[PDB]
Image (cartoon, rainbow over all chains, first blue to last red; front, side, top):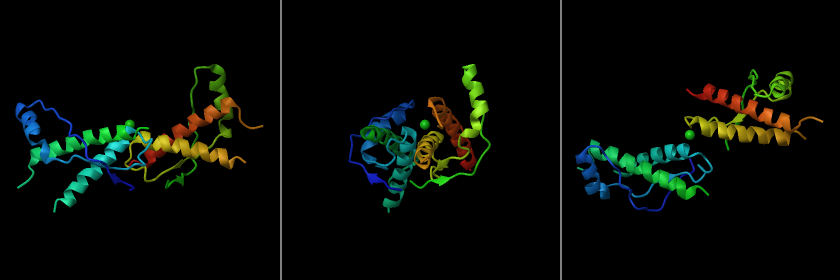
Length: 95
Length: 95
Ligand SMILES: [Cl-]
């Protein structure tokens, strides 16, 4: 439960097999978050535990905070960029 | 940090390649703990995180609490039985 908001970060490029989605992500990635919520304490915790929690709390926060925006495509792309940033954030933490 | 002492449990049989250790464990397993410390909250946490923590806290507790007993052999056997019981304890928790 002891989580913080991490610093803004470069959005990673996510790849898709479908040409449409692959290009859609590139053209729309500015619409997604560029920071994530995690637990500093998820330290030396294993990566999967940290990322599991970071993804859950981060997506939850964006649901609430977002008081015609997103479609099914955007939701899943947002989830993937959030996961990658959580992994990056865990590397930041490791030592 | 929110950990509990779990209920006593049947000691699992641990196996060794060395005939001496394999039999030593069987003849001396009564000398080791038969319960472990864990975090109920390490729930739906992944198994490795739960067991990582359970093993660490459990062995730490036995160090303190133990105010000519154990040798190098006993220490490592104790660690292995503790790990197995932590895994059992995590299965108890899973749902
Ligand atoms: Cl893992």
